[PDB]
Image (cartoon, rainbow, N blue to C red; front, side, top):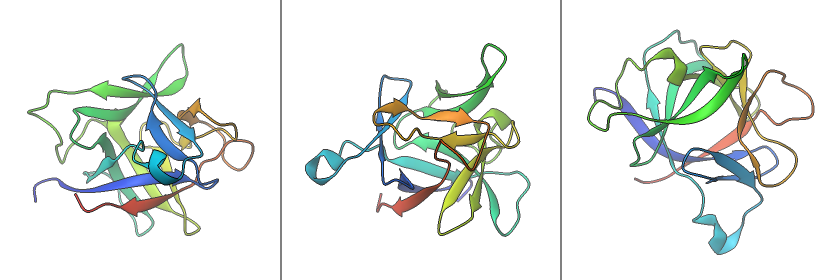
Length: 153
């Protein structure tokens, strides 16, 4: 298929699920049971960019929503945001760089690095119900690895 996609959910390494905060933010919280259908389903697209065996460029959109994770400078700092796109032009194989994340298979885990801001990663806090953000430091306080769960579309 022109741009190929797969539906999935992401969980941080502390088993926190992702849910929609406002219309333009994601939050991470400990969910289980019925409250699980609250989780965001992503449409991961395999876009063009520099690839390797453990580094694959992807675009992360919300399933059946014209909203994508984007990396932009805000108050002179790489920041994560959900951005709206023309529902007729996306997804595309050649997504603008702000939308591209390098999906890196490390442990049994995944890391999502901004293609635009090298060494800037999708991160979650240790604390409950805090927004998903772009973090510039791996290996400490904040969580930078996830597991992916495939959903049947």
